[PDB]
Length: 376
Ligand SMILES: Nc1ncnc2c1ncn2[C@@H]1O[C@H](COP(=O)(O)OP(=O)(O)CP(=O)(O)O)[C@@H](O)[C@H]1O
Ligand SMILES: [Mg+2]
Image (cartoon, rainbow, N blue to C red; front, top):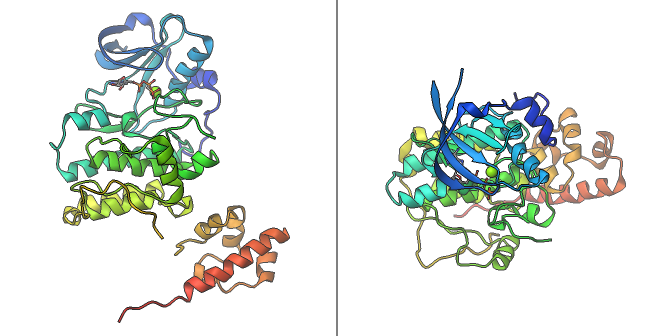
């Protein structure tokens, strides 16, 4: 559960501890439903001690032990999760060939392919509900201190009741074909700081979630499809952003833009995203106002106010002092603007460089708070 110790960096141990070894005789492989990286994927039935329908991921013959470890490690990770919007693991087969990962059956398959199949056949409210489910799954993952690093519509599965669940777990996931090498990551879904500095956090997952929102509201359009990967690199590094989908509520596109904030600290947390989507869903009239859709627009020009002290500290990469600011009562912004350099020093900022950085930032923050701009 959340808060308990996790095993995200030891695949074999996670397989031993958090997966159920299933006897091959209890598995019935039926039709082929897809092709994974490590082998074919089948639909089948599993007998437990009544038969239940399941998805069966197999490991190709002639595999290397490294591929076997990476394959079963996904199940080792999946077995630690229990949530409505996270793909559920039934078990594994590691003792006998072929290696198998057995999960719940998701009849409608990948979300992007599903939405392209059902182009325009859902209401806006239903799409928002799909996004809310994905966001709830991601909130659970963030609360489990698990960074997905590869959140995308193609990695969201849909069952016969249209429940959307996050899938695709593991560690060294350079395997996906969309990722391309740089400085191997799916650049069209990856936050700027994660492409430049490989800083993968839940905030970069929030960026990816904004991209997923775009994918859902467009019914599976490829992000930046007009642009090459190099042009996408320039676009994201310079502040260009995707335009609004057609028939997209203004609040949803604004949420997208919030997920795409250049500074990761300003992006909302997944808990905030779930709450926001819940509020929109309970008052569906809030979804009637649409963002201006221009079919000729393919990309938005770069865009040109802190709520928490932690947001401002992470802005200047001084988050390591955040706890020290709260513990001394400096919990508001209009209270940190009333700080002297000695107050900064006593709460535990000793390095002169950090003192200088914080002081220079406080000057600009005082400028911000005292700004007046009221149109007459
Ligand atoms: N639980 C499930 N229910 C129904 N179909 C499933 C399924 N799991 C996988 N599939 C099908 O198999 C396809 C690929 O599966 P999967 O994504 O797990 O392989 P993979 O993770 O190795 C690709 P990548 O490495 O690029 O992320 C999916 O597109 C999907 O159609
Ligand atoms: Mg996978």
